[PDB]
Image (cartoon, rainbow over all chains, first blue to last red; front, side, top):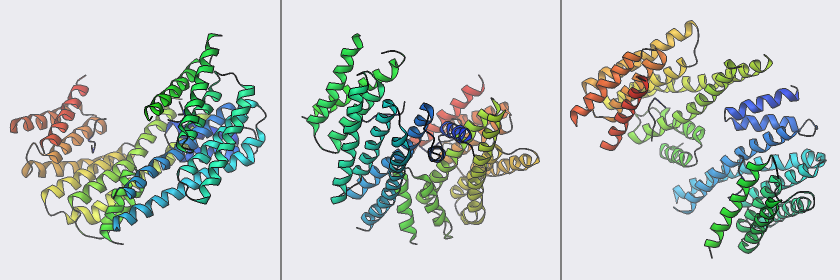
Length: 7
Length: 6
Length: 228
Length: 221
């Protein structure tokens, strides 16, 4: 849950 | 609406 | 590969959410002829529910896109049939295990009602994607499996047994969505709810499972009556 | 096949959440040789993000079961190596598409920084599972691509830009989780957040700045 998601 | 796995 | 090692790999696959691997492990456990234990019977049910459920969810989405849109229409149709195949192959695998191993080996009334409810479940899944003359035969196969399991549970199970309540939940869902009979669906769910409520005055160790299904029975009753 | 038919089949696979199909469709589009548009680029990023993400989640579970244990540890080990092989094959696929197609075709700085950030991410995924002397080389490959994207984004891209902010988020994650340098990770996320506030598609930018400060709150706790 740290890195970037894509929404 | 059916039975889930729990 | 022994059976106790297939079961362990299936439990590991459930933790890893690798359900295609889980079903393959439980399929090999079943195909060895030995009657499934309570845990192995649940592992097989959970594995194939997730496997069939992913294609069921994928089917409803691409089918809705195909309906709600010429060139793009075809691609939505062609892709939906590919999922529809996958979906049919999964159900036929389950119903093959039930017909050849699961149901013939069920020596207890609890196990027989379980496998017979599951047989109506996967014939219902086939009916969700069925059309024409084929659909009528599949629907009748689902109603006969449900109706059977309904009558061993009515004569061998208490009204608060989770398997009996869960079968009444799926049987009523069949009546509402597959047969388009909301009256038979509401009557079946309301009876199972009240019979279990009446018995609650006079169950143990299955507290959590039975009361959760009772809430789902009333949840479906609420939604269906709203569609007056 | 048609490139447009492949793209629209990939869009169909997303709504159905069949991410292996979407990646296979998008991999064929990338292999045609043309520079990917912004829409095609995001479809490819979303695809492989979900394909490798499923194996990453599975690996963390089976690996943790293996260490947190005799006979059971054997199957848990064997199962993790099987998942690790799947994850290695997926990561080698993305890095190959970036090496032979995507990065060389990148004309804009935007197209660049995005694909180098991609390269650093999928080496970081390989570093999460690598061990031994092979891990040392994988870690340096991730930092090399991360650094190159960071210096380019500092020159061209505005501080409130999504991919510039998104690269700083993943680069700071690389320092904390791979290199175990929390003070460097906290510093990188702080200046990136503070430089974005200096300037103040705003909705996409402010989401990442919240994520950057979210990591700062966690790491300093």
